[PDB]
Figure (cartoon, rainbow, N blue to C red):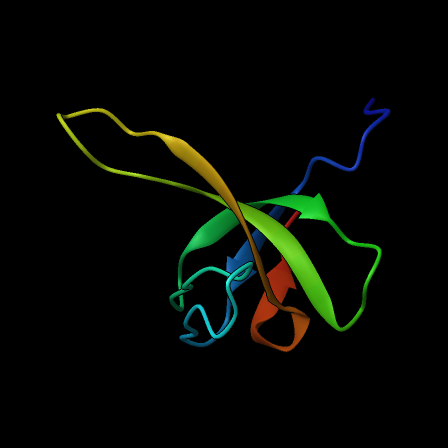
Length: 70
């Protein structure tokens, strides 16, 4: 049971941060669904890398280059 829209989506094709609010995506990379109120573009969350520590960051992406998994 889940009372939230916190799902996971997989990247279909390779994309880049075309906008200052969008992030770079790569085919095969799965991100966390944050905003899905826009069939056009969807807001996903990715992880960073530094000092052997994986951080977290949000970013918008084209819904035309993504596919929900769960």
